[PDB]
Amino acid sequence: HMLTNLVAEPFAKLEQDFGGSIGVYAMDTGSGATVSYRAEERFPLCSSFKGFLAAAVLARSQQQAGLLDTPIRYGKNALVPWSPISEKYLTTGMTVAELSAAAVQYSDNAAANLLLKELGGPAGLTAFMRSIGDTTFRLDRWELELNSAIPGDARDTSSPRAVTESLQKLTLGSALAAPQRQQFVDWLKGNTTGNHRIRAAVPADWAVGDKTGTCGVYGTANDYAVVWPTGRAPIVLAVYTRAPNKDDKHSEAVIAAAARLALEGLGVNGQ
Image (spheres, rainbow, N blue to C red):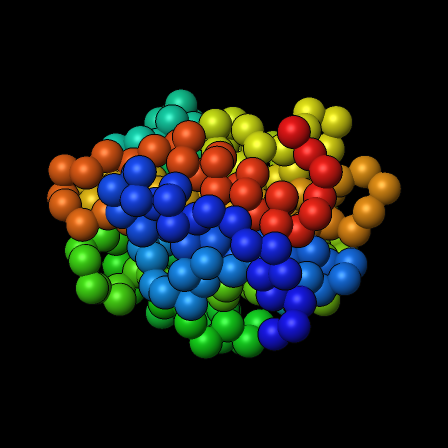
């Protein structure tokens, strides 16, 4: 309460210029100060669920030794659009760990669906999120159907706040054992799809890991990240967007701009 939005930032003008809605939740893990704008509204996850998917696989690997090393062979029928890594290993297979890295770092859709199957589908990932205390997250469908981003549809959504809270538990808290926690961080740090989103607001000499999402309709796209500014405690944040019309385009620049405002609102000296 008293540490939320100590310093107001012009999020309303930003979303109005964008032509839609922006949801932001950012937490300074040192002081607990927060920046919050539409933070409890639902937004479509799009590919951003794939970070939590990888975390769920890591959690399972704590009880199933050798899970990560398991080789997975798949057929051409598994190769749904935008599977840039798994298409290169169709004739060989990939390990569970490699599928998880591809899902996180390249948003690989075939990899994501293969890992969802390992967990028992969308309900199995939802169950993992419930097990860490997230009552907001819901995954309902598979790739690519989960990208429909229909206004008012709660399927395949979460809130910026719940995304940030869960991300903090998994990357900095105790939801994963220490080796698995660092592996999750390392996968997020190696993401290749986020250079124009939260990372564009983060100075080059700070460490950062992130996971993006882009639905392709309804101006719907997002990013969440852990950021390690030097000399102070890490920041966790989530930035989600949507817009009213199916053919409204998303904007990476708006996500970066919202992240800049969040860091400014937390008093973190950055760019």
